Amino acid sequence: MLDAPTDLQVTNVTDTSITVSWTPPSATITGYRITYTPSNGPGEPKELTVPPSSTSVTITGLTPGVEYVVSVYALKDNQESPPLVGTQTTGGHHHHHH
Image (cartoon, rainbow, N blue to C red):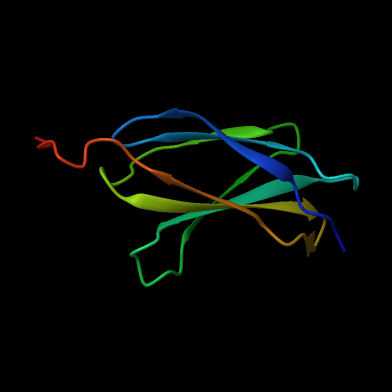
């Protein structure tokens, strides 16, 4: 049972992407799982995974102009931490797209 990563930082944001960084937990870890969904979505999210050497990830294909909830879970084998949770609105709310 595993402590959560800390200090979610958004280092870049576009109309369709977010770059997400975090600080590792104190535990030995074997990966991270990242979920993302709009706050206004039914709420079951999309999921990605990364190796433990990744303490940042860029999420693409996002909807412009909406608040996303990003949740980062540390993994240790079959085990997962509670998530580190932060929010970010993508660019372009008042702009057309294509």
